[PDB]
Amino acid sequence: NSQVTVAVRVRPFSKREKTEKASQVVFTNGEEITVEHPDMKQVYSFIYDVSFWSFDECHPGYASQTTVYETLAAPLLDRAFEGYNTCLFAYGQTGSGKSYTMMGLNEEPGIIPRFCEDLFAQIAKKQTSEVSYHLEMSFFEVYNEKIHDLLVCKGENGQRKQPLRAREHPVSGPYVEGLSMNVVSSYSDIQSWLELGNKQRATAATGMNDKSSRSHSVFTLVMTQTKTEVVEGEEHDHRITSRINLVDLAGSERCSTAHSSGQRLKEGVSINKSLLTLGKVISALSEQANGKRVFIPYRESTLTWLLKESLGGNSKTAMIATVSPAASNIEETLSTLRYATQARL
Amino acid sequence: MREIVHIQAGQCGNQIGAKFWEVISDEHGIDPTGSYHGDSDLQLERINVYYNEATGNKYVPRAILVDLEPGTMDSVRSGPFGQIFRPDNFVFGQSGAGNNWAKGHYTEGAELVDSVLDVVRKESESCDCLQGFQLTHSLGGGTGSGMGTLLISKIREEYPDRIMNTFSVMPSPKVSDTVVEPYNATLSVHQLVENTDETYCIDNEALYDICFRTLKLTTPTYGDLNHLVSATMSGVTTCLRFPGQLNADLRKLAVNMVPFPRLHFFMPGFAPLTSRGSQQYRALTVPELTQQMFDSKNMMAACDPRHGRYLTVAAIFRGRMSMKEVDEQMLNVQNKNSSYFVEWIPNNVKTAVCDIPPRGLKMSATFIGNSTAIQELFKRISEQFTAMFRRKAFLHWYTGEGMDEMEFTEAESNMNDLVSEYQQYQDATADEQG
Amino acid sequence: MRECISIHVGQAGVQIGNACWELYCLEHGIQPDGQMPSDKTIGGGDDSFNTFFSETGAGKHVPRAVFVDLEPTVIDEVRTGTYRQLFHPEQLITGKEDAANNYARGHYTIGKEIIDLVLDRIRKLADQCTGLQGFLVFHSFGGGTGSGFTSLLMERLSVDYGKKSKLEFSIYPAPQVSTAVVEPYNSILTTHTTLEHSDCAFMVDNEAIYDICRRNLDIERPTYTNLNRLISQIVSSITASLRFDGALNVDLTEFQTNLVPYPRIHFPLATYAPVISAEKAYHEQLSVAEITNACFEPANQMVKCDPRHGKYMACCLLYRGDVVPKDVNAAIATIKTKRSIQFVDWCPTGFKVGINYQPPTVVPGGDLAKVQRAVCMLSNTTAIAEAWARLDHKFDLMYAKRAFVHWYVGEGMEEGEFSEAREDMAALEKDYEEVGVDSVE
Ligand SMILES: CC(=O)O[C@H]1C(=O)[C@@]2(C)[C@H]([C@H](OC(=O)c3ccccc3)[C@]3(O)C[C@H](OC(=O)[C@H](O)[C@@H](NC(=O)c4ccccc4)c4ccccc4)C(C)=C1C3(C)C)[C@]1(OC(C)=O)CO[C@@H]1C[C@@H]2O
Ligand SMILES: Nc1nc2c(ncn2[C@@H]2O[C@H](COP(=O)(O)OP(=O)(O)OP(=O)(O)O)[C@@H](O)[C@H]2O)c(=O)[nH]1
Ligand SMILES: Nc1nc2c(ncn2[C@@H]2O[C@H](COP(=O)(O)OP(=O)(O)O)[C@@H](O)[C@H]2O)c(=O)[nH]1
Ligand SMILES: Nc1ncnc2c1ncn2[C@@H]1O[C@H](COP(=O)(O)OP(=O)(O)O)[C@@H](O)[C@H]1O
Ligand SMILES: [Mg+2]
């Protein structure tokens, strides 16, 4: 069956922060995470299935990138070859280390490059001249409950963001029309597509940061292992297929502080509704793993509706939340750790 | 300035509207010339919620007729209250849907929807503030199912901030009136579930049984059935028009009747209903009304709440009442009938009161309810549906008009998932210890 | 002179104000047209009482009030009623649409587009006032306007006016009775925001007042026009020393002091014992002892909670009419001799006491009777924590499933505010349990 694996990663202080000398609010005791308000009145504790401490190297249990890949992502690539689907969530507010854990810098690579390179270097080993592995990639977004494709090059006009629609095949399940799928042979082709997509992804210079991710983003890889019938008849026979999804979600965007009106407010509403439905889905899946028959509300959002076969049944889901230990972002860290907290059982 | 736009689509919709605009025009004092001939002064305060003003202090309703055959147009015009509607709002065509959801959603409705939207925009932009929309439509046939749902989908896109109520006449268990009811109903639910906020389900048979067992009517025409539907329509929109002690609206009821956005299919009902002879031998008090409203034999949905659990109910009272006698009564129901309700919602009842009742009664009441018994309304269709779809019975008349088999399976799966969502909350199980 | 601004937010607020000002207009002698008839006598005078009514040179007295509802249905009954010529025409409707019992709407979506226009009027009234003291707010935990808009306004007034008293008179939610499914959310969300700004919140409940109107007044079918008349008497007893002469006078800052030990336990109750009919106006002496004992009976509380399940921390006792302090001292001695009425060890000084000479006025069409002596008891008791334990549990039921949350998110809110508020209330429960503990070093 399918349980989830929620993890937390505390980013270290920026040199700007320890030069300005921001104070520390997020502490740990190996297992648990603790938040202590600067007033030192209330202290809240959070337990998770895994906890990553990237605060300082000299600490015991330092959480580098290679121990995030080996801990969360790699057991999903392992389940791929077994013939099952997998999804990797990535939640986090701006200035918390989402793109350092997932994509990474030129050095210190995140989950995407390590994952892809291990996949390619392992199919290079496993292929026998009687088995063959074919990979097919896709990359799309969600904006106000509308599906947009990114890898297609958009000439400048009003905008060519065609609102594609989702359908439900009886066997294959929910899918996306017009999805420009592409082929891949090694990791140096995914970099190009992802750069070309992230350039066209939606952004806005809201109050928090010069560029915030105002849209979700699903990056899918479909593998097909063809092994041959020679009972008597050659293949095109046996295609065990697996979908591996890496989703880069957006922020919750409390609108009390952010006096947001119009399009930014509508984007915030859509993001928060999607995240609520996703939380409901994860909680229902954990309950199901714990022996309770329940109804997983997939059809209340597109993100949950298209990934239905990738977070259900014989599937393995993973989630990583990013937090800052600074005292100017306590109100964000609290909501993040409390969004993650309702997935752990 | 909480303005409503009534859209009437099909025979059912127009025949309910021709009775509803007789009920509201009476509740506000309008005559078939469009002129105020009333007595009070509250009738004029919030007449803007349904009507618009003209030159000679005339009041023209904000109605939009949609039907694709001229027969109902003439019935409205050649009628009692026909010369108050705007002729530029009698939108219609010829060669109707043919009891087909495809002809009225892709072929013939697409050739006329622009003409309806051009009137909708005119009547919505002439409103100071808009509360929502209002559609009366029979799914089971064509036009009301297809050309209604398409208008819903195109208004929700133009107005994804407003309410879109749908007062629908669903098909009945025993006796059908169209052979292709299952397909069309399934394809309408697939559009309403995704593009509605509060949809009210009505069934001819529940209303026949009301007319026979309560009202003691032997031969009730449809003007009698629609006389019950209009009553509930007016009950929902009384707080916006008239004043009251504890008020409500469409948004507040929808907030307090929809825990999850998909479960917005409700059972309407109205009290006090009685036979003309058994009026002298009853008392007009709140408990009699509460006993009449929560009675299974007073519903309109043809689905018994004894076979399910109420998730959330509403009660819009009209008259000079006492709020203590509403609180006590609506607490008594939760306690005496705890099994018929949900535990993770402590108080399932909403109350609203208006200080101005219906023209002939000292007191009135209107009842909405969200029950798991309407499961039965869909589980039947999905059983009628798949059988036919297991043989491809009447499908070549829909494919020919530009449809695919996938659009059927999608709707079927959506309905069955709705069934599961309602059935998850009707087996009362307990917690670890508490 | 002294001045107190009243802010009636929501349906409940307006329907309480329409009785409160009905009462004030009679206590002082103002007709609904604003024109005092017995300004014949003034030759100076101060009976154009400046605590509530601003006078203008034409012989007219306009109240220091503000109305806002997010819906015209209630305010437009004032414009069309008997008191249409009294209030300044700035009775602020903004009722293109109401809060739909959503805190998310009355805080940001529709709560804004207004609050500038409310603050511009409060500023206009304050500048017309010299020694302003206090903001009497009137609202309801359970609706969207009263919940969110009041939170917003109290956030703003804590910045614009700073350290000035803010007394909330709030309709508390009842355990069993409820006219809405989303009071458990709005109540907690309003407490989370108002708790850091308000200074004393006087709570009431409709169920208790129904029980009173049944048992004492002999009304089996009562409506809001009976309850709000009693709430008006509570406010008048609170606001009597600032208008009429007395022996022991009480300013608004004295409730903020004698009844708030710690800045988060400022949620007291209210009580008004002589709620007897004109029939039972006879057959009873109606002395200070009988009344003071009635106010400590758990049945005549205006909030549904048994203080036998808790401990009193402070209690103000405001009396009107022919009272002598010897009687109050004897009564308090009788109450302190009783063992069912427990107190905290750290509060041996108990009761605040106040006396005013002018007795209450009877409204025509009312249910109260002319009584020579009146009393109002406002007590802080730990027992109300049990009520907070109820609301916090309902929340826990219909929030585990995230029911009704998409309506709040759809109007500008986040899934984390609920957790924040629930944790603040769980902290307040522990803060109510701590003080009950007996002191040991
Ligand atoms: C002397 C007297 O009391 O006559 C009553 C009457 O006998 C009864 C039976 C009326 C009567 O209604 C019916 O018999 C009936 C027939 C078909 C379908 C539904 C009802 C009545 O016709 C119906 C009529 O109701 C109204 O007038 C309301 O305004 C109603 N609107 C209209 O009837 C109406 C019809 C056409 C044109 C304009 C208005 C209404 C109800 C709810 C909301 C808005 C309006 C009333 C009180 C009566 C008669 C006349 C006998 C009842 O009607 C209602 C809705 O309450 C039927 O049961 C109630 C109980 C009443 O006692
Ligand atoms: N005591 C008393 N309570 C009232 C009165 N009117 C409404 N209430 C209570 O108010 C609660 C709901 O809050 P409302 O006042 O209706 O909400 P609102 O302020 O009008 O805000 P909206 O929801 O936007 O209309 C209910 O539980 C009622 O019991 C009244 O006149 N007197
Ligand atoms: N309650 C009610 N239902 C009706 C009435 N007229 C028709 N119906 C129902 O509505 C359906 C009529 O379908 P309709 O849309 O008129 O077919 P169309 O003319 O092709 O659009 C039938 O299934 C009837 O059960 C009416 O006056 N009252
Ligand atoms: N574990 C870590 N060690 C060192 N630096 C880190 C770590 N995590 C995050 N950072 C720093 O924090 C920044 C994260 O920015 P980024 O996460 O890309 O913003 P956003 O979250 O808005 O995408 C990077 O510049 C990186 O240098
Ligand atoms: Mg209101």
Image (cartoon, coloured by chain):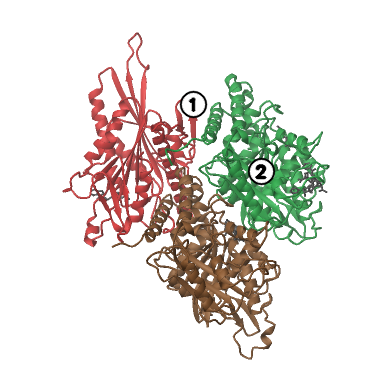
Left or right: residue C271 versus residue B145 is left
- The chain coloured green is B
Name the colour assigned to chain C in the rendering.
Answer: brown
Q: Position of residue B192 (x, y in %)?
A: 59, 39
What chain does badge 1 belong to? Answer: A
Judging by the rendered image, the residue that carries numbered circle 1 is A170
> Toward the viewer: B74 or B7?
B7
Q: Position of residue A181 (x, y in %)?
A: 39, 32
Name the colour assigned to chain A in the rendering.
Answer: red
> Toward the viewer: C345 or B349?
C345
Against A148, residue B355 (above or below) is below
Same-chain check, marks 2 and 1: no
- Inspect the image, locate mark 2, and give the three-letter code of the amino acid beneath it: Leu
Q: Which mark is residue B135?
A: 2
What chain does badge 2 belong to? Answer: B
Residue at left offset 57%, top offset 69%: C291
Q: Is residue B186 visible?
A: no
